Each structure stands twice: as C-alpha cells, then as structure tokens.
Amino acid sequence: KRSSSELRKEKSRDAARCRRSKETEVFYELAHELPLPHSVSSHLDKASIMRLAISFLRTHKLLSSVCSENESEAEADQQMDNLYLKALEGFIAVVTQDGDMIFLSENISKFMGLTQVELTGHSIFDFTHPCDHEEIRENLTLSTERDFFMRMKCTVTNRGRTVNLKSATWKVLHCTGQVRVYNLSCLIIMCEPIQHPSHMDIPLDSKTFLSRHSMDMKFTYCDDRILELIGYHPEELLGRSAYEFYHALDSENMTKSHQNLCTKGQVVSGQYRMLAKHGGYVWLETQGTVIYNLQPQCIMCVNYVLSEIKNDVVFSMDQTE
Amino acid sequence: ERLARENHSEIERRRRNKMTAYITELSDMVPTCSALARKPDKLTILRMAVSHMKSLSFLTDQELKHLILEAADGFLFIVSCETGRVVYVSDSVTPVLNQPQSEWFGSTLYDQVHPDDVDKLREQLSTSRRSFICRMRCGTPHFVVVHCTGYIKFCLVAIGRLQVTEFISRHNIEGIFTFVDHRCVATVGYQPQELLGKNIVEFCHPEDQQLLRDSFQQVVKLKGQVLSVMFRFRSKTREWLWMRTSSFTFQNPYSDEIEYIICTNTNV
DNA sequence: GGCTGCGTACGTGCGGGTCGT
DNA sequence: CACGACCCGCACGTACGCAGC
Image 1: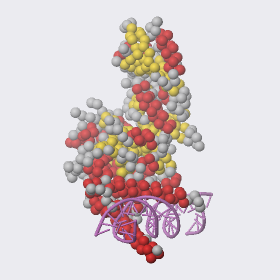
Image 2: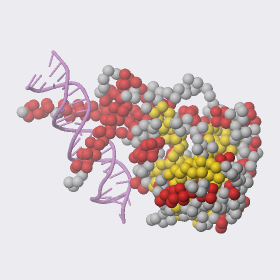
Image 3: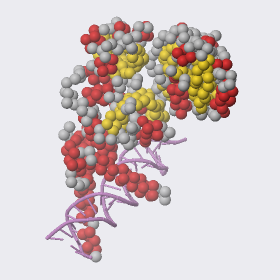
C-alpha cells in the first residue's frame, strides 16, 4: 500500500506547511502592530511577541480599571509628563500575582543594563537572586503599602558600560510602592539601586558625612565633619559598636537594616535618631554597603543628616559623662 | 553525542508547555475569546488577538504619570537653580502636602522647606543631577519628611515623595543602666541621669530583688528569647510601683555576641 | 470499522546566534 | 573572523485525537 502511503502524508506535509505559513505571517504582524517601533518590533523573537502582547494588554487592564480614565483627557500639562519620566532616579515595576513583570519602565536600561524589550512579561523569579524569592513572594500579596529590598541581575558593572546576561552581576534594589487590585491584584513599585561610595555618581554635602565600620558595625574610620554637626570627635567612636549610640525605639529597625546588610549587599535604613555627645539626638538616614576581597572585609556608610538636635534631654551613659 | 538528544527533546517539551500556556494566557485576555462558547483554534485565537490589539512606546507619559503617582505619594516641581523661586509644581502637591497651588506656585522653595534646611538646600543648588532629603510644610505646624529626586538644565526639575504609661531601657549583663528612655520621667518620675551610671536592683523591692538578679541571669541564658518579670519599684515619691518588664538579650546579627539587654518596662 | 478534512503534541535536522582558551 | 565549543529557536514531517457523508 504505497499507493495509499502517497496520499497519507503528502497532504499532511504541504497542508501543515500551509498552516505554518498562516501561523507565522499571523504572528509577525501582531509584533509589527506592537507599540514598539517596527525597527525592532519586526525582527522580534517568536515567544517574546506573546510576552509583550499579554503584558501590554494586562497593563491596560489594571490601568483602565484603576478607573482613572473618565476624567483622563484633562488633568495636567503634557510637557511636564515628558519631564516626569526623567526626574525620577530608579525604574518602575508593575508585577502581577505570580510575578510576571507586565511592565518595566524604559529607564531600566540605564541601571540594570537589561531592557524592558527583553524583560516585559517574564517571571520575576528568573531575574531575582534566590534567598530573596520568598521575601519578594511575601511582598507580592495580601495595609497595602510595600517597602523592601531585592537582588536583581545587572549587566553594566563598575566601569563596563555594557555586558551580556552570562556575566550577571547582582545589583541591590530599594523597592517602594503599592498593590492595586482588579479582579487578583498587582504590585506597583519604584525600585532604586543604591549608589556605591567609591563610585559616587552624585554630590554630597557638608551636611552629609561618611563613616566606615566592621562587619559588626564596630567603627574603623570616619571623617571629622561629625563634630560640627553632632558634637562627636571621630576618635571617640572607633572601638564602639554602632548599637550603643542608637536610640532604643529604632534599634529594632536598625537590627532589620543590619541583618539585611549582611543577607543582601546594601541597605538604606529608616529615618532613625542618634544620641549626640550631650543632650538629645539627631535624625539620620544611612546608606550602607559591604566591601569584599573573596571574602567580606568592610562596611562603608554614607550618612545623611536631617535635622538639628530634644536639645538637652540625656539618654545614655555616654552623655551622662 | 548521546547527551544532547534527551536534553533537547525535553527542552522542546518545556517550550511547548510554556508557549501553549502563553496562548491560553492570551485567550482569556482578549474579550472575544473569553466570552466565546469554547476554546477557539489557536490560529483564530490570535487572529482575534491582532484584531483587538490594533483597536487601541508601551505607555504614554500620562499613563505612567498616573502609574508612579500610584507608586509614591509624591509630586513634580521645577525651581530656578540659584534664586530658589518656584517655577512649576504638579497638582499632586495638594494630596501630598495640603498646599493650595496659588500658595505654592508663588513661593520660593527656601520659603517652603524647614528653616535650618535652607542652608543644606543651597548646597544642592551650586553650579550633573541631584537627589537628597528635606522637610516640608503641611498647612491647614507639623512638617513632613520628603525625599527629592531631580536634575539640571536655567533651572532644576525634580520629584518629591514621602516615605510611608510605659518606657524602654537598655542594660548590660550586670544590669547597669546604659540607655534610658525620656518618657521614663512620666512613668516613674525620674531624671535619666539619676538612673544612668548605676544598677537597677537597688530600685526593686528587698523581697523581690532576687527575682530580678536571677531573671537577668535567665535572660542572658535564654539567648535572644523574650521573658517577662513582675516586681516592685521605688518611685521618687517614695511610693512603690508594680512592673512587668519584658527583656531579651540582643546579640549582634553578624557576630551573635552580646550588646545589651533590652527591657520594655510597663506598669501594671 | 473504511479514508479523508481538521489540529494539537513529540522528536529530530538545519541555520544563525555567543562564547572562550 | 576564524573555529568546534556549543545553545537557541525554528520548522518540518509526522503521529495520536475527533468531526462527518
């Protein structure tokens, strides 16, 4: 039965080929349509087209059902939004329940190297360091405001400009946002990377000072602009662990910050308060980063000061002197 | 050779699972399919996809304005680099600060921050891009902590966003008062310096003080774990006060070595 | 049970990608 | 700009699951 065989699969060959033709030509026009310029929307990977399509659509879904439309036509100047993009420093993630990054901002390239073109629609846990996957997982569901840290992949490095995925350095992200709902929900966070002390990309102040400590927050060094602000000589604080100066009402949160600093790479602590050499305290926010070899060696801190000094009220046996 | 075949066939299987799941993900996203009686031919499914897509980069600056407002209580403002006078402010200034725009628009940024910050303010205005932290007004004075993020082009453009009966004491292993809360004076009528530099048991009652000593012994013994102790305590009115003190050993997150005993002292 | 239109799932072969020493 | 090293995506041919004159 070769006379039967010739009928069996020839039809299958050319008809399945015909379907494959339909299929393809039907996909690349979906891609063509995409908000992206035809430049790249055209020569785009097969599956990624689906990613971007799905993402785009869901994004518009939650967006529209934030209501936030019925008065959408008139509300603010359009030039100012052009500038609204740029003024931020950090990127925006719109991440679903199961952690599908249905929107990453364009600014992302500038920080993570990777583009949204490569990421929009992909699962978050692919790109995030494990040991964080569960922290993130907590932050993704169930008030509504969110504030935490996560380790994400980066392809830019310290003096490199550009890199590919294989060479994924881990970059730490301060994530701050909300969780909107449309029936299932969606996390909306601004992520901002923490800038390194040696690779300072922005200006400090006299109002902002710098210290170096051991891995247990025992000091190693600090510049002398401390005195002018809070009244301590740097040399009075060297052997001292950092917890002995912390106000009590904060040291729990400071514990959180420190154990984060060990478990991740960097931290931004809350607005805590630190006891002066004499009466009272000063508000403060420290940016901490760990320095390796390869083994953990040091911790360096960019301390931002916020206010002046309960000027007289004594708190610790250091002030009592 | 004989280690690629399996690897690939299973890679392929993974791809099929993944992708067909992409299709059935898109199916319940386009109105037409989700309303439709049953599942349509994949091909026709995404025919419908294209047709719906066209019926609408990724988001307009308006959309993302909306988005990042719903990601941060915050607003945009523009100020001339070295005079301080405000040039623009987004409406979002009102749901963030309670400030009428007729008020905020005329003003100089210096006349809107916390006074002693003005110095720090001009430091951040001397002629890349800049980012820092300040305190701002509230109107109807309780000021609010505002993070700020911007750049330079002439003037500066930026975005501000806000971050969303008892008394506490720290001792060392001996019980020596190391840190003392200020609200203590309400609690027991004492001045912290009359507390710092000396032990705690001499404030406890003669027939209770052992409970203190050996409880501290347990606190350091019970490494990290909480435990409460009730006892009687000399006020400065000579009067005695019952006290539920909850204490636990703080050991350093990295070194797990003692730092101090944290006791939250409550009256009952 | 024939044998065909109609479709989704499995495995292999071929071309164009990126590393690495 | 080489070269097997490959890894990835791609389509082809095909095999099992369901309609119906």
